[PDB]
Image (cartoon, rainbow, N blue to C red):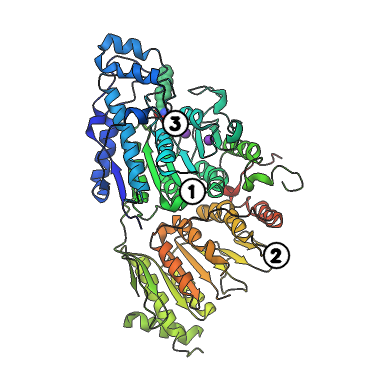
Amino acid sequence: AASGSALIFDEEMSRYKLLWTDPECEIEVPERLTVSYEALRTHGLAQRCKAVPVRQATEQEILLAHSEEYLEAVKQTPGMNVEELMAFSKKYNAVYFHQNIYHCAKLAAGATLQLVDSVMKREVRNGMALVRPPGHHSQRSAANGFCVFNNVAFAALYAKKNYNLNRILIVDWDVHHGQGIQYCFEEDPSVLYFSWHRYEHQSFWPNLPESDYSSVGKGKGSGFNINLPWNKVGMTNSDYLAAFFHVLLPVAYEFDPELVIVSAGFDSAIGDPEGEMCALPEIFAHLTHLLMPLAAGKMCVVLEGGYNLTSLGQSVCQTVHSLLGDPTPRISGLGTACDSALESIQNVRNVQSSYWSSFKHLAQSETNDIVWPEPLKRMPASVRTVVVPPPGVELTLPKNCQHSISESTAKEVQRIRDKHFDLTDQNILRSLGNIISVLDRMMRSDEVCNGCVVVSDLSVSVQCALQHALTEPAERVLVVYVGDGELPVKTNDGKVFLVQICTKETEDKCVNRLTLCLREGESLTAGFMQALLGLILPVAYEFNPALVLGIVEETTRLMRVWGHMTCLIQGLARGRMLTLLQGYDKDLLELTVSALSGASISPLGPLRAPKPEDVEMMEKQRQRLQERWGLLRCTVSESW
Ligand SMILES: O=C(/C=C/C1CCN(CCc2ccccc2)CC1)NO
Ligand SMILES: [K+]
Ligand SMILES: [K+]
Ligand SMILES: [Zn+2]
């Protein structure tokens, strides 16, 4: 399977610049490329990426997305003097030309195609192209907003033509609306385009009516354009995550793209003079991470904007850290999106309910100088995942997993056995040695990250796992439990939150438990995904645990989704998750280790839309919990 991450960059694309004064374009500088690549080098991330050379987009490739007339006129700019380049620039909105910009434009476009080829030829799993000029504003016959050619549109057109792709997701998290991309694909259901952007009721550039939430596509492409306008500046991590959990991710996993392309502008990051938003660079580590289980990880991140040379470097690194599989930073202080964001979110959801399953219950009333902390260090664990299979069972393990028991810890198991258990089943007592040994390696060391242990007795294993974590001390523990029955977990001191996926409808009282009973049947897979994206993830992120404890009991149905959840849930607790599998099940154990270890998640494909009973159940849980956990909100709250 493909491994590694490409980094496509070339110093030549920094060799064009503004040659006259124009405060509109004053901010698009060569140093954005220089600073971004030099920050990747400073943090050791460039050295870990497969360098892939830049190339020029050919004339035929340029014409996938642009007209002959426009290409001919741009082809003349290398021969123009400064006076002539200014006259040519003035024909377009917020764009400057330079004797070398045509050359660099073909490089920025060729680099994107180099990226697309390396990912689709399985030479790498994913990658990033640092390019200049940006693309997403470019249109079929015009330059616009610093863009000459539409790099990301090329990539989707080229991947369609050269790899026969039917479904391509484009995620545009730049702070500006990528109207060039939207115009490109508005009638094309094969390309799904998502963009959030500073709109301010159309008063922010490029001031377009069709940048609003109501542009859902045209014709056969209706429903494959999703605009989320930001009508206030200052949007926070919670707004960005609320957009992902309640708009982008539900749509993207139902669409099931064969390739993901990110228009990665970082002007949506704190400190940027254009975006004036407040999201920390670390949020881009999660934006990337939450998209990585799509399309078996085939993700092409293409740089667009980003103008604060400092927030720029830190967001590029956070993105590449996640592309490389490094553990995610903990995001603290999450809560409800602001009212403006919930308004935009609720309006997109409503207008899109005609087109997407995860929104369809909405349609019938039966169913309805700036400073911030420098990001902490992210270092890959030397051994990522520890595994403890049943005694004697050896398994073919990924190159970053080991099998598990010191006398020091063997003392601890005696101490616990003497007080709380009596227990003499000397096998269970090995389970407890394993849990403690794995947990100690997970939290004490930065060279083991997570782990899975097979166990026989759930309650004693769960108890010591939980009690040993709560005493390290891990401030908070998220517990995710697939099974029925009550476990020895006391989730009423604020330190534990319990997600339980069961088969019997059990009323839960208090707001530190989320219990989901999904009616059995073929629709079980889609219902689980809907609760994962819309409930489990929003709560888990607000909760912000220091350890995640997964628990599966021997009583299959889970095998189709367990890998997505294991992958997504590693956005919490810096990836520190300990999974207890009750009984042996080589396939469940292989899948868990594979997702724990950072491998690609195989796609879900086409799923039967979820049962309405399950969607009423999950909206009842959201009603019951969103007042405590504001990140669950996807509507504006009732003003009393
Ligand atoms: O990063 C991008 C392009 C971002 C551009 C958009 C257009 N404004 C210029 C608008 C302006 C600025 C100052 C005075 C008068 C007008 C600059 C930034 N897209 O992702
Ligand atoms: K955008
Ligand atoms: K489209
Ligand atoms: Zn931008």
Residue for badge 3: 276
**Compared to 489, does 191 lie above or below?**
above
Return the disc, 2 or 1, that comes first in the chain's sequence. 1
Gap between marks 2 and 1 measured at Cα: 29 Å
Mark number, residue 172: none
Where does the image place residue 497, in percent across and percent down from the top left?
Answer: 55, 62
Whether residues under marks 2 and 3 lie with C-beta atoms below 8 angstroms apart, the answer is no
Gap between marks 2 and 3 measured at Cα: 44 Å
- Left or right: where does residue 294 sit relative to residue 315? right
Q: On the rendered image, what quadrant is the C terminus found in?
A: top right
Ligand 4 is within 8 Å of the C-beta of the residue at disc 3: no
Where does the image place residue 592, in percent across and percent down from the top left?
Answer: 45, 66
Residue pictured at 24% horizontal, 35% vertical: 10
Where does the image place residue 109, in percent across and percent down from the top left?
Answer: 34, 32
List the single residue furthest toward the right: 366
Q: On the rendered image, what quadrant is the N terminus found in?
A: bottom left
Residue flagged by tag 3: what amino acid is it? Glu
**Compared to 196, does 410 lie above or below?**
below
Residue 97, located in which quarter of the rendered image? top left
Residue for badge 1: 333
Where does the image place residue 398, in percent across and percent down from the top left?
Answer: 34, 66
- Left or right: where does residue 270 sit relative to residue 478? left
Residue 554, located in which quarter of the rendered image? bottom right
Seen from the viewer's position, the closer of residues 101 and 435 is: 101
Residue pictured at 39% horizontal, 59% vertical: 599
Return the disc, 3 or 1, that comes first in the chain's sequence. 3
Residue pictured at 63% horizontal, 36% vertical: 347
Residue for badge 2: 507
Whether residues under marks 3 and 1 lie with C-beta atoms below 8 angstroms apart, the answer is no
Seen from the viewer's position, the closer of residues 601 and 528 is: 601
Callout 1 crowding tier (Cα within 10 Å): few <14, some 14–19, many ≥20: few
Residue flagged by tag 1: what amino acid is it? Gly
